[PDB]
Image (spheres, rainbow, N blue to C red):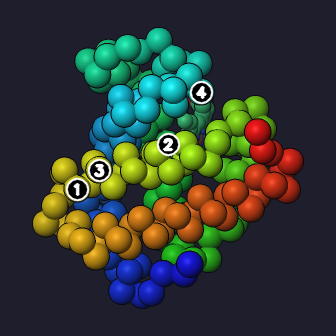
């Protein structure tokens, strides 16, 4: 499940593109998640009512939350397989009040690979897509281990 140094280099390289506009990337990721998987939308009190891509873009809160999501994920990814320190608070909040199924983690991960493909193809070739998919599977897997401790499944 671990990533090779090469795979980590592929991940960090593309994250460099996200670094320039974390909020804007986060916005596009959530929009991709919400449009492809509308049931995910139901887990956000604030966004449950945004029916359209224009409405989602018009939401300042959605963009700000997008920033929040990718800022955290950025933290995890730059730690490269020594990341459980930032995972605990993430697992804790996605498995208690919220209750976010692992499969929704998969979906946002797909949304992430999709946005990076579209926006940064020259920095996201096959191996890099492979490596990011791995980094993100590792992340879900680790969170899912913490979900059990937190007593979450359903
Ligand atoms: C890479 C995946 C994700 C990351 C890094 C992430 C990160 C975060 C962070 C940092 C917060 C705010 C503080 C906290 O609660 O820990 C948060 C809150 C939240 N997360 Fe996530 N999240 C991810 C995936 C998801 C998904 C897929 C969903 C639901 C479909 C979700 C649902 C929520 C909700 C509903 C909140 C509170 C929203 C609010 O009050 O605005 N998260 N998440």
Mark 1 — residue? Answer: 117
Of the pair 96 and 62, the residue shown nearer to us: 96
User: In the rendered structure, are the residues bearing label 4 and label 2 in contact, judged by CB atoms less than 8 Å apart?
Assistant: no
Of the pair 24 and 107, the residue shown nearer to us: 107
71 lies left or right of 91:
left
Of the two numbered discs 1 and 2 in the rendering, the one whose residue sits closer to the viewer: 1
Q: Mark 2: is the Cβ under 8 angstroms from ligand 1? A: yes
SS assignment at label 1: helix
Residue 27 visible to the viewer: no
SS assignment at label 4: helix
**Nearer the N terminus, badge 1 or badge 2?**
2
Mark 2 — residue? Answer: 68
Q: How many marks?
A: 4
How far, Cα to Cα, is label 3 from label 4?
21 Å
**Nearer the N terminus, badge 2 or badge 3?**
2
Of the two numbered discs 2 and 3 in the rendering, the one whose residue sits closer to the viewer: 3
The x and y percentages for residue 30 are 40, 36
Image: 146 above or below 54: below
How far, Cα to Cα, is label 2 from label 3?
19 Å
Specify the quadrant of the image occupied by residue 9: bottom left
4 lies left or right of 86:
left
Local crowd at mark 1 within 10 Å, few (<14), some, or many (≥20)? Answer: some
Q: Mark on residue 114?
A: 3
User: In the rendered structure, are the residues bearing label 3 and label 1 in contact, judged by CB atoms less than 8 Å apart?
Assistant: yes
How far, Cα to Cα, is label 1 from label 2?
21 Å
The x and y percentages for residue 90 are 66, 50
The x and y percentages for residue 120 are 18, 58
**Nearer the N terminus, badge 3 or badge 4?**
4
């Amino acid at each position: 499940m671990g990533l090779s140094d090469g795979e980590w280099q592929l991940v960090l390289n593309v994250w460099g593109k996200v670094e320039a506009d974390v909020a804007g990337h986060g916005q596009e990721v959530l929009i991709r998640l919400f449009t492809g998987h509308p049931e995910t939308l139901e887990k956000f009190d604030k966004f449950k009512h945004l029916k359209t891509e224009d409405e989602m873009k018009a939401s300042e809160d959605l963009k700000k939350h997008g920033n929040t999501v990718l800022t955290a994920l950025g933290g995890i990814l730059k730690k490269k397989g020594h990341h459980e320190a930032e995972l605990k608070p993430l697992a804790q909040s996605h498995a208690t009040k919220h209750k976010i199924p692992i499969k929704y983690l998969e979906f946002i991960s797909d949304a992430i690979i999709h946005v990076l493909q579209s926006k940064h193809p020259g920095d996201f070739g096959a191996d890099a897509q492979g490596a990011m998919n791995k980094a993100l599977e590792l992340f879900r897997n680790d969170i899912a281990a913490k979900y059990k401790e937190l007593g979450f499944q359903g």
